[PDB]
Amino acid sequence: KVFGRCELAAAMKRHGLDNYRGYSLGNWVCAAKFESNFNTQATNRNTDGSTDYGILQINSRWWCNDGRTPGSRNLCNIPCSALLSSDITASVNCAKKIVSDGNGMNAWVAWRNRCKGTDVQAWIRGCRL
Ligand SMILES: [Cl-]
Ligand code: NA
């Protein structure tokens, strides 16, 4: 599922990500634009050989099970395939665990590098609120 911008925002707002651990909805919509271009089926290999999956590019080393990443903790209890759904619940439950854990949203290199320090309200301009 390729989400529209405001379509994604409404889905993420409905799952309570708004100011979850202190990150306004716009941070999450920005993290998805750039992690996945709003695409639930997205995958990208990483050089450690791990893969990043779903609309927030959740990584198989630490967070889901993809049957090919040494030495996987599957700290979310899930198959990575399941994060590629149209439906975003499993990805949003696991993202809530990641962002808690220590480093906040800096767990997303794309957030750091491209969202952080910006007006991330532009990402929910024009959305029914
Ligand atoms: Cl934080
Ligand atoms: Na894992």
Image (cartoon, helix red, strand yellow):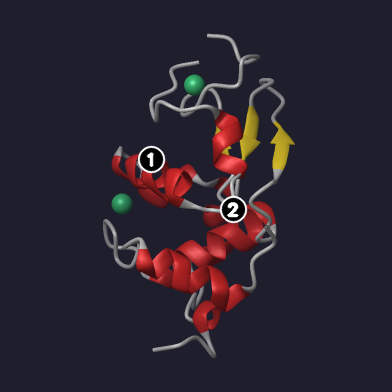
Residue 120: x and y, percent?
49, 75
Badge 2: few (under 14), some or many (20 or more) residues near its Cα, within 10 Å? some
Residue 78: x and y, percent?
46, 28
What residue type is disc 2 on?
Ser
What residue type is disc 1 on?
Ile
Residue at position x 55%, y 66% from top?
30
Q: Is residue 91 left or right of residue 80?
A: left
Q: Which mark is residue 33?
A: none
Q: Are marks 1 and 2 in contact (CB under 8 Å)?
A: no
Residue 116 sits above or below residue 107 on the image: below
Q: Quadrant of residue 75?
A: top left
Residue 45: x and y, percent?
73, 31
Residue at position x 43%, y 17% from top?
73
Residue 99 sits above or below residue 60 on the image: below
Q: Foreground residue, 49 or 85?
A: 85
Q: Is residue 80 left or right of residue 77?
A: right
Look at mark 1 in the image and give the residue it sits on. 98
Q: Foreground residue, 33 or 117?
A: 33
Look at mark 2 in the image and give the residue it sits on. 86
Q: Is mark 1 within 8 Å of ligand 1?
A: no
- Single out the mark in the foreground, 1 or 2: 2
